Image (spheres, rainbow, N blue to C red):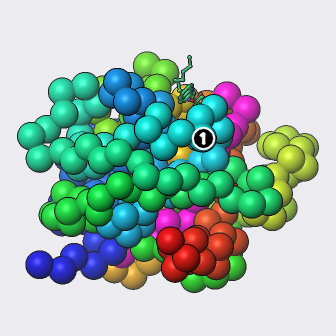
Amino acid sequence: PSFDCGKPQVEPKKCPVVGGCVAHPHSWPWQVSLRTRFGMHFCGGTLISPEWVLTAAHCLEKSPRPSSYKVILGAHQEVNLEPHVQEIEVSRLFLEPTRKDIALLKLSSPAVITDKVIPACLPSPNYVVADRTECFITGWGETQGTFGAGLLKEAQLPVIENKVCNRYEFLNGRVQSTELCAGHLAGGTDSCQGDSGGPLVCFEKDKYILQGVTSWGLGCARPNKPGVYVRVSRFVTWIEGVMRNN
Ligand SMILES: CCCCCCCCNC(=O)[C@H](Cc1ccc(OCc2ccc3ccccc3n2)cc1)NC(=O)[C@H]1CC[C@H](CN)CC1
């Protein structure tokens, strides 16, 4: 039973995390929860192959010990995990070598790929997501009064091209070429604390492609303050190299 990357078996709501909506369970089957050995959620991540999870380097910077971490796959509820959820210990950590905010976790065992646990697709190397492309972020981060705490949420965010995002009114030059921006400039919808390390995916014809890793922002969901994501396409060669070498 082979499953194509980026093709959920439960079609997502795509409601047009603060704002957005609670996802249909298992409609974002690459979303993982990165947890302490005691089962405390602290970051998201994205399954990109049965043995590999992509996350933000800042999620791992406190401990270089793989035993500090475990990965929860197939979940919908944060607290009361579903019976099919897989909990897999991390074997090795690989931080991006130029110190950008992206990292790989090699799992101690491959995840079992099912209709609820499926990898996201990687983008082509150096792909640029065009201004205004509609994408989605997912996670179990905080909700700032918008409902759904404790459940996996999604939010539709359009990409804001870097040259726009860097304007004074927005992020005032801070965004690097190895980052991208996404958000609604009227505010109200955004990734927030506890979402970092998770995916920003953009639908292309018949599948979702992982274009961003939730990284940072100036608060959550503020008007004129879109979130910043690591631009995954600038790291595909590095990611593929790590997977090939390990
Ligand atoms: C006492 C703090 C414990 C951390 C749990 C709260 C996690 C909340 N996460 C954040 O604040 C992360 C940063 C963060 C901080 C700490 C962190 O993990 C701490 C940690 C994690 C594992 C550890 C293992 C052994 C020892 C200490 C450890 N400490 C992970 C992520 N930033 C974000 O989620 C961003 C997402 C984009 C948004 C704008 N659109 C703004 C917020």
Q: How crowded is mark 1: few (under 14 residues within 10 Å), some or many (20 or more)?
A: few
| Nearer-the-camera pick, 234 or 144 | 234
Q: Position of residue 120 (x, y in %)?
A: 39, 67
Q: Is mark 1 within 8 Å of ligand 1?
A: no
| Nearer-the-camera pick, 232 or 37 | 37
Q: Give the range drawn in magenta.
A: 207-219
Callout 1 secondary element: loop
Residue 123 relative to residue 70: left or right: right
Say whether residue 107 is magenta.
Answer: no
Q: What type is the residue that disc 1 sits on? A: Pro
Residue 68 relative to residue 125: left or right: left
| Nearer-the-camera pick, 246 or 217 | 246
Image position of 147 with respect to 243: above or below: above
Residue shown at 35% from the left, 45% from the top:
89
Residue shown at 59% from the left, 48% from the top:
56
Q: Position of residue 127 (x, y in %)?
A: 65, 79
The quarter of the picture showing ligand 1: top right
Q: Position of residue 169 (x, y in %)?
A: 85, 41
Evaluate whether residue 122 shows in this view.
yes
Image position of 22 with respect to 208: above or below: above
Q: Name the residue under label 1.
A: 64
Magenta stretch secondary structure, dominant: strand
Q: Where is residue 28 in the image (x, y as percent from the top left)?
A: 31, 55
Evaluate whether residue 156 shows in this view.
no
Residue 230 relative to residue 165: left or right: left
Say whether residue 209 is magenta.
Answer: yes
Q: Please, which residue is most extreme toward the top here? A: 145
Residue shown at 29% from the left, 31% from the top:
78
Residue 27 relative to residue 174: left or right: left
Q: In which quarter of the image is the N terminus?
A: bottom left
Image position of 141 with respect to 178: above or below: above
